[PDB]
Length: 225
RNA sequence: AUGGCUGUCGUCAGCUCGUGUUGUGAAAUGUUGGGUUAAGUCCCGCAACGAGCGCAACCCUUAUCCUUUGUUGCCAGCGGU
Image (cartoon, rainbow, N blue to C red; front, side):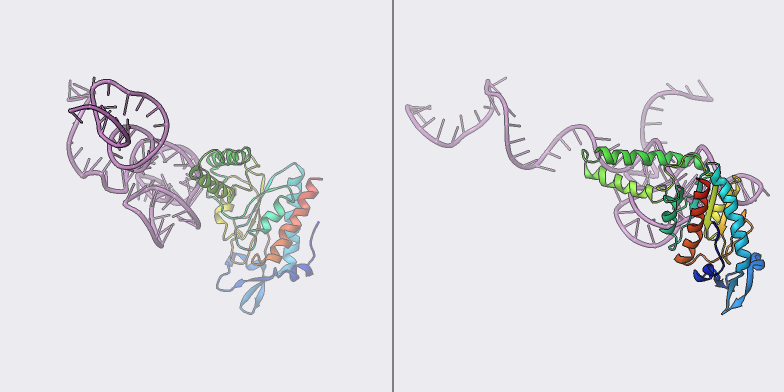
């Protein structure tokens, strides 16, 4: 249910950012400065990695629903790969400011969406003009581009897994105003002071991210057993 | 002192709200930006997400044809003038 040290070195989780982009609040996680870029100390990661998955395993044991939030080009598809396979929810393209804190109004949008899939199956678009049809279908891809992963959820999730905390300060802050636990893959540029459970590591690699959420897909299945 | 009604800015494209969020606060954000349009018209991006009054459309008339009717309307195809 855990990962080893050498395979993490294979995915390049030690390759952080330059010294021109590091957040001074992560000095306890910096080994040294090789080639002018900070290198993450791996032996500090694995225990904190297990502190995260063990905590996430109990949340998954009580029939809990977690959220996978990754917006960058690396996890634009990787997040979805884990989601439906691990029976969870997600967002991968656009995080609407006020997705959880303003859940009362965004819930209006998901019912607005579920009407579109229903009208697309029975044959409601093939009785009216293309003027009203094609723009309504373009409204359907617009709504599934963001709400397509949390349409079949209902209510705000129990926990939350986020990638690149710097790029998702609007996401983790919404969980802080609710008290929802945060499991972040914090990088050298991000801030660790807003996360409940930090995991120092690189996120700018498709093989690195799949090593992360691919592993948490196993622990969530351990909770669903 | 007012209702009703009316002009005007101006048929100019703007004016706001709910919720969330930022700020001690007045307020801001949304409604900013890149293009576009007659138009916060539309698209993308975005701590914004949506909704309403507007704009547009639905109304009337005019320009084309078809179906239906032919009086007191009209005169091609045929007779008497």
